Length: 83
Image (tube, rainbow, N blue to C red):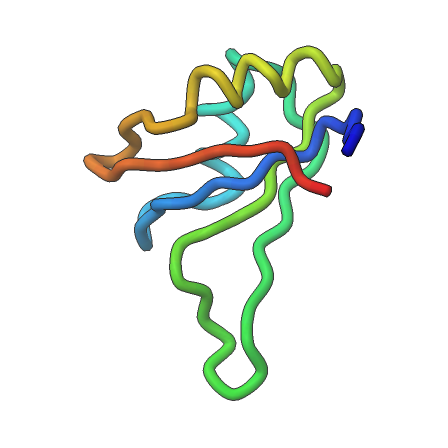
């Protein structure tokens, strides 16, 4: 309950999306500040998910309401406020 943050999660990506694209893609919805993509140790390869951080907390809501169930690189992505 009560999250109050700006870090969002992207679900439904491909091998074409990255922090670079997320930066440009999510910048209109809100000027991103940080983007982190975790990996494994045995495979060191994600699946297709990342974290988007915005400079403005309210800006994230836009990415949330804009990227949630949207289309990116021909892929359906889902966004939500981290916690």
